Image (cartoon, rainbow over all chains, first blue to last red; front, side, top):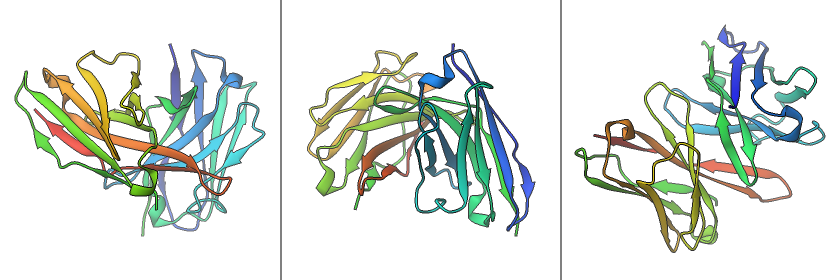
Length: 118
Length: 114
């Protein structure tokens, strides 16, 4: 059974940085694409970042492209999301998701909330 | 101009039948979408992948009461014999590689109350 566990959220300030982690288990981490998807207070879902099996390719929406960095350490079975120059608009619940074939978000984590206040 | 417009939130009485709509933007009427279900305070859950011909494959733990069909730019999620556990927000999403770069749009979501 697949398990994804996020960590690292909390109350932060605009301009700061924060790094989120997602501990994976129940599957061979290195054999799958991993993603980060967030849900804002208004309930809207937003894809935030994607990384390939061995970390060779990464893609982001133009909304976070120059501020967020997705990375992974396959030896630790962990996915990361480095967030810099935090904006109020970054306030949301962040989820890590694992794909399956052509399906992007086949498996989701529990989510960690990042609250940016101003 | 990739957008997904979803039908309005509605309530259904246990045992009833529900049909939800997710409309693709005209230029992408032949796209394959994904349906996600999110129950109160819980993580979204993968429901199904739905193609232009209405064919689909559901996720694990999905009751046979959930089916999909299509009609042009419309993508439908049909919930048969509505149960309590079905109360949730249903969001559709669609991926695409526009300018050699990933893109993924979600719909506003539709809340189903029982």
